[PDB]
Image (tube, grey):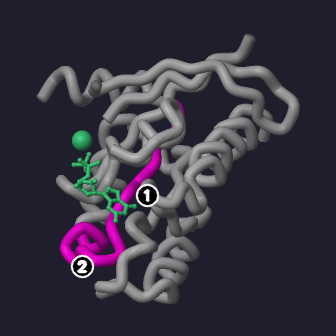
Amino acid sequence: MTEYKLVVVGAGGVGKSALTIQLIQNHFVEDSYRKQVVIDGETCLLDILDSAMRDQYMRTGEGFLCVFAINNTKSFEDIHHYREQIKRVKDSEDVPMVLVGNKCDLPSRTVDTKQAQDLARSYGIPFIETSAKTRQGVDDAFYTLVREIRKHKEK
Ligand SMILES: Nc1nc2c(ncn2[C@@H]2O[C@H](COP(=O)(O)OP(=O)(O)O)[C@@H](O)[C@H]2O)c(=O)[nH]1
Ligand SMILES: [Mg+2]
């Protein structure tokens, strides 16, 4: 079956681990994960990972979940750095990515959905708000990234 190498990036504390645990273990709170799921009918295995070893993992990774938290303006501002690093290490301008705004269950929002939608539009990538606590958007975020990887492999 097809294997998809995913890498989750973003500032500390945004919920990268919480998100992946919710996806894989189905509960709210390991540096890597491996599970078989069915996405759009295709059975596939998700291999997920949250200096030279970092670069190797980025070269191996086929899609990147770029995570900020809606209550962490710095983490949103840092997205550009993470995106630029991935493009540099992979030496490519077309890298499958999804922008994730996590912790959308919390009331302390400092990043407006519109800001994140505009950023994702500039990058040409999908944007999805998630909550690792309530599971809102979690499957959609990872499955959307897999769909982005497919389009890149087909087109
Ligand atoms: N309310 C809420 N807390 C979250 C969410 N995601 C993560 N957290 C909490 O944020 C803290 C940091 O999460 P963690 O997954 O360790 O962040 P990481 O450093 O990005 O891997 C923990 O206390 C989590 O329980 C979320 O969607 N909602
Ligand atoms: Mg973590």
Q: Which residues are magenta?
A: 62-77
25 horizontally vs 42: left or right: left
The secondary structure type at the circle numbered 1 is loop
For ligand 1, tell me if the residue under mark 1 lies within 8 Å: yes
Residue occupying image coordinates x 18% and y 53%:
12
Residue most extreme to the left: 51
Closer to the eye: label 1 or 2: 1
Q: Is 114 above or below relative to 74?
A: below
Q: Which quarter of the rendering shows the N terminus?
A: top right
The one nearer the camera, 19 or 154, is 19
103 horizontally vs 62: left or right: left
Tell me the kind of residue under disc 2. Thr
User: Residue 141 location, x and y as percent?
Assistant: 58, 53
User: Residue 28 location, x and y as percent?
Assistant: 40, 47
User: Residue 109 location, x and y as percent?
Assistant: 34, 85
Q: Which mark is residue 133?
A: 1
Residue under numbered circle 2? 73
Residue occupying image coordinates x 64% and y 19%:
36
Q: Is 96 above or below relative to 75?
A: above
